[PDB]
Length: 265
Ligand SMILES: [Cl-]
Ligand SMILES: [Cl-]
Ligand code: NA
Ligand code: NA
Image 1 (spheres, rainbow, N blue to C red):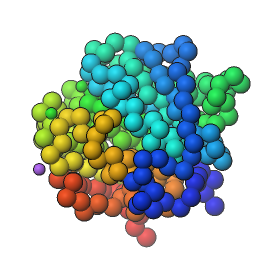
Image 2: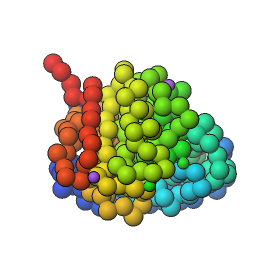
Image 3: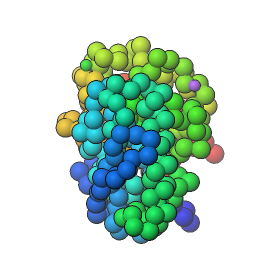
Image 4: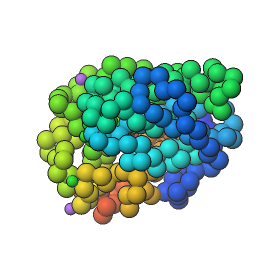
């Protein structure tokens, strides 16, 4: 059997729900190591060690913009750290360094007997997410650390759109009407540059640049897809292959693309 499989068999309803099967607690990081601030969300009853995901905001933004992912993912069996950057005005490369520093510190806390996450993390299984420049930073993290198991940035931007070196399974959430990082000049060229990975592009119909942030009105679909992608690729959990790889065939999705996701016999 798959040693990383956690939780009950998924359904559309169970993945669209506000909360997954596991009870979630959280704590503030006392002394951030290489980033500004962090909140760690974790399941108290996942029944085995789980992977870790680090999530970074966009320019000027704070944990609030990305917070909803913490409980949503942790409740399905992940340790999730949402960060504030050293400065709200840090650029993508710095955001990537800080994201990886947050993953490092989650690994440290996994080995710290006083930590609520002591022994809860499989430090070999990690993922990266983030908004806008924090999404660009997630793609930089993946490019520089190919042992990461999944990436799922939202409304990404970087000074370069060429992420051809990314071999990590990558889901790009995009926002159709984004006027900050227009899809046609940012998210879509980024998607098209990646040639060696499992990848997906999911654009929310009518979405502004904040369409995947806390308080969005598509938490059922966006949360289903983010959880399914992380389950499929961080846990190798093929119970999630359809949810991860499918076109939702949704009137809420103005553009859907995927490649190298479904397995061919
Ligand atoms: Cl930004
Ligand atoms: Cl916008
Ligand atoms: Na690259
Ligand atoms: Na539209």
